[PDB]
Length: 182
Image (cartoon, rainbow, N blue to C red):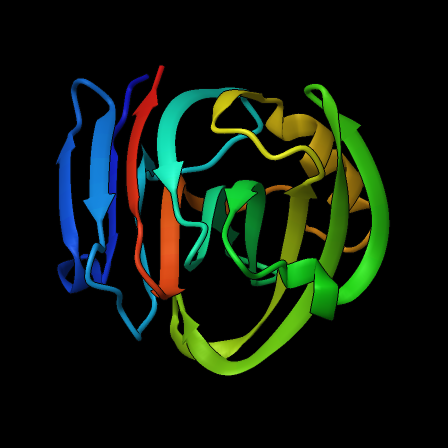
């Protein structure tokens, strides 16, 4: 992997363990949470290389994602390639951009605008891009490039990347996750 960055945003709301040199991490939020966490492992600068992962992920009670997650500095954007998830589909509610096919499934693609919300520069206004896998799974390869190229026709800057990680996020309910990046 060449993992050089640990993502920890409110990981203390649950039990986050990781080992950078093995590329593994776990997160348990068995009791539930009612605030947002995002944890995981990755690289201080994102790129379009494929990511292969393997996970156990149990969050059917939970507003949660298992996703490639990362940011672009300018135009400021937060992005997700959601491989599996719980009770909430961000594309149910956001503006639809269409569909992309990659790595064995279609993904619905959507975007949203967040105003004065926490971001890599503090509090600011940014765009979100989502690809949500139609056949959810917890192991495989994500050909990031196919998503970036599709989003780029819709304004995604597709360069000037900040961090990028394989992540678990939850903001409600309980669940459990253990992930290896290969």
